[PDB]
Length: 257
Ligand SMILES: *C(=O)[C@@H](NC(=O)Cc1cccs1)[C@@H]1NC(C(=O)O)=C(C)CS1
Image 1 (cartoon, rainbow, N blue to C red):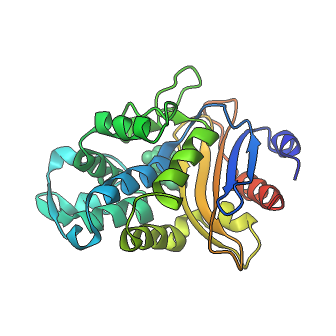
Image 2 (image 1 turned 90 degrees about the horizontal axis):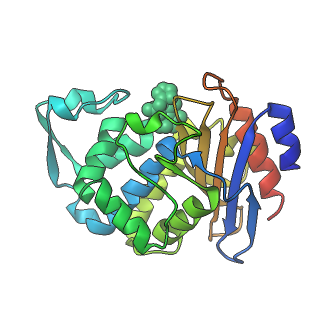
């Protein structure tokens, strides 16, 4: 459970921010250090869009052409020359971490500039989106591009989703995708007590074993979630991450609640 110890064990860097939204209790570790957020940013973009389009209006369709397609888009590559609903874009983004879906969501919101405008409004002067996928995944310790600190990122997740302006239907739609997202099973989901519910979105940048998971964690018996942000990376560009590191970090942090 000592986070200093797990860093030793895994020869890795750990960034943690956790907020029990009922009590307001926080757990912090390297919470002001920058990390590539990678695909965990898809949760933020999806929520921003859901602030803008009511659930009954998610049936709106967007046209997809060959220029929209970027790598690791298992769902969207099938839509070239076809239309897709905003509902299906978000499902593709959240469940399959589809990059083309996330890019389209950012475009629908109005561009990177508009995401930045919303983050500043939520009081986040830290989270720094500069590029679209997949380029945002090329992390470099020397650059702040597409990085955030566990604390800044968690505060924004809390304001946007936990204590924010989404309707009951849009919040349920988005948290249900995160709850049912099986791609996040080896991460926070793996380290919390088995009777906990975990709604997560993972991330992995291409470099420095940048491996992350953010989630809304519900202790059995509590309906208010604990917002949990875990960002990790290692010293070498080509290092492979070990998901167990995130699992063990979550197990340790959750003992604090
Ligand atoms: C978000 O992190 C996305 N990552 C990338 O596009 C960079 C990589 C491609 C292959 C390996 S890294 C998507 N999300 C995830 C994830 O959330 O775990 C993975 C593994 C790749 S696509």
